[PDB]
Amino acid sequence: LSLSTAVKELVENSLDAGATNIDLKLKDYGVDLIEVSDNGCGVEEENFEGLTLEALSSLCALSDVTISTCHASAKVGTRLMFDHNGKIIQKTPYPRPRGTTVSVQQLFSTLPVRHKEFQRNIKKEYAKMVQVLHAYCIISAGIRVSCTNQLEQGKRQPVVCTGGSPSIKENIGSVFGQKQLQSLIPFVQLPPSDSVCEEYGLSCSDALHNLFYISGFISQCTHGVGRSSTDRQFFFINRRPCDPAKVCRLVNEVYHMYNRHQYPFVVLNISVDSECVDIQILLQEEKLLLAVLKTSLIGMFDS
Image (cartoon, rainbow, N blue to C red; front, side, top):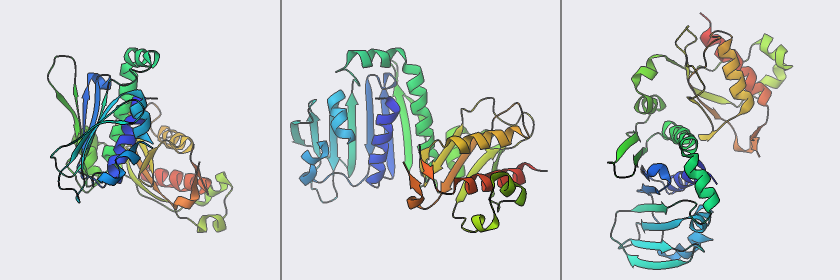
């Protein structure tokens, strides 16, 4: 029942549509409006009702939901207003490009307690949403992801925007500026060392079936170069944003082994077999993953 959850589900809904453009429009930090527009495949007319049988149903139950959409097979798009039961109040033709735009109006208005806790704690929830959106922007190469905000009677201001660049590094540049990029080194994967294998109780036979492909960027261990907090640490598994506790703790700990007083900027993707993942996300041979991680981090930060 958080802002970042609804935003994330709408974003992944746009991604599953194959959208190359994803725009977020917020009014009063999302308390007033949370809108997502994408050029995805749109929704066929056949599955209009079936959309509220998932994010859409709960969003209808908790807010005022409007959806415009246009499928490639459709001659004209459609505009739909929903009541709180997910039942379509209005279905009118609506000319628009291929894709889908979902509008969430006055979130939590049907529960005044949750709405008020939302308004009073707007800064924290807003910041969490910011972190999630940063993760998706960083990991979504080839896609244009943008976000703007409007407060009260003020004019709209842009929050973030990527240019559909093909590389994660350029996305990081677009999100945080190239000044952030100057202090970053790219992750370089290494086989696990014998000493780290000893530490984690692993033989070479265990390390043989290494199927973890780690990538990303991390702050240099040089004094002062790192960050003062963990405000810019992003982890993914199969390009999906997540927060692995042991992996994060090992990352920050190994960084402290060289830069005691600072935390690193982190962007780290773990490519692994999806069968080896389960639900906190469980990873088969996670000790091997931590061994490769520690060995590689040591190899990079070592002069």
